[PDB]
Image (cartoon, rainbow over all chains, first blue to last red):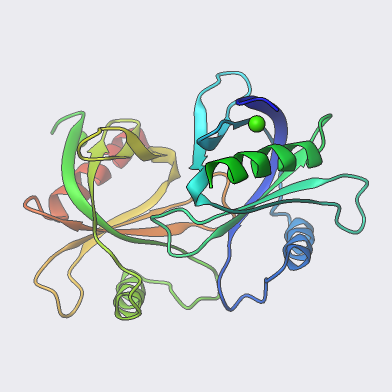
Length: 130
Length: 130
Ligand SMILES: [Ca+2]
Ligand SMILES: [Ca+2]
């Protein structure tokens, strides 16, 4: 428990989810992440992920300026997963931003704190908010 | 000419552009906007669009808080268009955000100032920046 916590993570990829792309489960999403990675579309970018009781914020690790923010009302799902062929956990966040026609899948690689700890924190903040 | 100007607009829709969706031209995009609208996916939301010499910013018309921002380096195209069956101009902005796997199309309805005036301002700011 902490109202505001931060974690350093590496953002790996954000991609839109359409009703006809065949991507329906966390597992389908991890598989599309591995395809993307084999096409040279995934490049790790270090970021600061901040969970507060009203939103999840992403910041530049040095400048501390806000790169993106998702109010908790915009998060539709948060999971942590270890795809086949990886010793690590990925943090998956699906958001439906109000202005966008489709939801997006965001994948993050956790560093020392893993994705499981961040998943519990966001899910605790979601339960609370909701 | 003005380094920073603002315009009130209505955001209509933002959607991702994929290499296999058949959407290649401004005209294809206006047609997909009309399909979306006939599926009940388009709802006008009033916003403040600000052009500065380093970025395009979208704000809530009252609270003035930033809703989104696109550094000029992220804009790949800006056009104004009058689709068939409309007496008005739409402002089209295509952006490729660094973190996203695909570019997005954003459509805005201009109000009293039209989309043509905003297109020239962003294109002037793009030329300058570039
Ligand atoms: Ca917490
Ligand atoms: Ca200007």
